[PDB]
Amino acid sequence: LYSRKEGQRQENKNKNRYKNILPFDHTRVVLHDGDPNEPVSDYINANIIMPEFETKCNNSKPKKSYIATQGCLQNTVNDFWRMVFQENSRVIVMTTKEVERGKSKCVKYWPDEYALKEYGVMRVRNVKESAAHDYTLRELKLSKVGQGNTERTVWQYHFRTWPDHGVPSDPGGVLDFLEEVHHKQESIMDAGPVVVHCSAGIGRTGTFIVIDILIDIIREKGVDCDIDVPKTIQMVRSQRSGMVQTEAQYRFIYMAVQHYIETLQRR
């Protein structure tokens, strides 16, 4: 029995970018510490994605997990930073421009270059922006206003060259990007889930997360390991509905997996 009841509540209606794209109750990110003046303060349109494989062992838990979320709305920016803080996330993957084809996809939820901004009780300083070819890396410092020993670096990997229609015609850029994200995440002791967002939090987000999951398997278990793309996609869809939206996205996943395997072989 699945449900999306919290997302459907009237107190949360302005917190969803699309009225019928909602988080499953059983995997939604529940925000425990917010503004007691808000009718509901525990809601964000976001789900934890935990890779689940029939052959997982008895530990806590998968090596990497993700938060799949929508692009911020002006009124959910403070919620977004509460989520990042609460979950101890240290890496954010933004897969859209702020505006594409004249349409806002995500509000700018981070400060201007070298600026600092307060978002509710959260304080963020933009320390540095480094532009690579397909992406910009922003080094952010996140802390809870008033509290000592809460500051932590959050690395925002902003992929900027996804085409306005369709998907990249070659997956090399996305794979190089994910390799950097992978190494940053492992460089930070006990970092929380990697936050990944697009606009609705399902199409591009699902494409990036499913590739990262498959690549993580191949990076570890080798070129000859068993890969089942449809089963991995269904596994992720059990945790957030609609992950991977189009035929081009679905095929892009296959192309990326094949490309990654090819890269390793050439070494």
Image: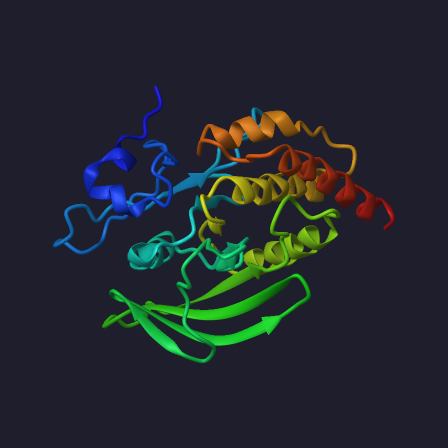
With 156 as the anchor, is 264 left or right in this view? right
In the rendering, at what x and y percent does residue 260 appear?
75, 45
Q: Outermost residue, right direction?
A: 266
Along the line of sight, which residue is nearer the eye, 72 or 237?
72
Along the line of sight, which residue is nearer the eye, 224 or 139?
139
Q: Please report the residue visible at 33 percent of the width from the left and 44 percent of the height from the top.
A: 16
Q: Please report the residue visible at 75 percent of the width from the left and 48 percent of the height from the top.
A: 170
Vertical comparison of 228 with 202: above or below: above
Q: Outermost residue, left direction?
A: 37
In the rendering, at what x and y percent does residue 49 appear?
47, 39
Q: Assign the N terminus to one quadrant of the image.
A: top left
Vertical comparison of 182 with 8: above or below: below
With 210 as the anchor, is 227 left or right in this view? right
Q: Please report the residue visible at 59 percent of the width from the left and 30 percent of the height from the top.
A: 232
In the rendering, at what x and y percent does residue 9 appear?
22, 36
Q: Outermost residue, front direction?
A: 102
Vertical comparison of 230 with 154: above or below: above
With 222 as the anchor, is 177 left or right in this view? left
Q: Outermost residue, top direction?
A: 1
Q: Please report the residue visible at 55 percent of the width from the left and 56 percent of the height from the top.
A: 185
In the rendering, at what x and y percent does residue 20 appear?
36, 34
